[PDB]
Length: 149
Ligand SMILES: *[C@H](c1[nH]c(/C=C2\NC(=O)C(CC)=C2C)c(C)c1CCC(=O)O)c1[nH]c(C[C@H]2NC(=O)C(C)=C2[C@@H](*)C)c(C)c1CCC(=O)O
Image 1 (spheres, rainbow, N blue to C red):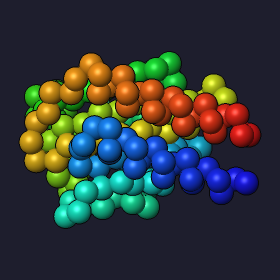
Image 2: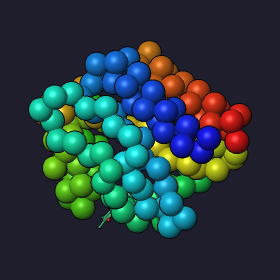
Image 3: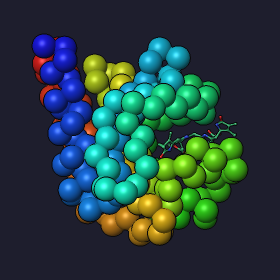
Image 4: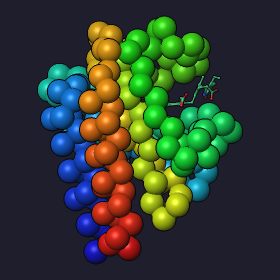
């Protein structure tokens, strides 16, 4: 029952990477300290795997929880041109991220986590249709989980 959650997470990451033809898609799920765990991952062969990593970034609890709960989407063509400072880039470096797309998963009016896509090693001008499909995907999976209780 509760473990059926995982089936949804696996679907989101696999479908997401297929939709975007990007290098990695993860579900990054928050605990009650807004520490995120990579609970699911679809990653093309040969790129670093983030699955099961716990990645604590205080920026979320300090700055961004409500914004994402309210539907914030961050598309980034080039992480080196996005005003992201070294303390941010340091987290993305090991995973070879160069472009990314962050969309929220909101369940029962609470920020469950984020669905995140990465393009490795090259910038990527995310398209309107790509952002819309990816955010839809996160919203759909969230609504399924919300309806299953
Ligand atoms: C907030 C922030 N961090 C992340 C992290 C990730 N992006 C990914 O792709 C992945 C998977 C590998 C992770 C994890 C995101 C998406 C955001 C939100 C960006 C936004 O919505 O604008 C954030 N963290 C930092 C680094 C900060 N954290 C630290 O531990 C230290 C030290 C830091 C130096 C300040 C920064 C700079 C941000 C954005 C600005 C901020 O909130 O301070």
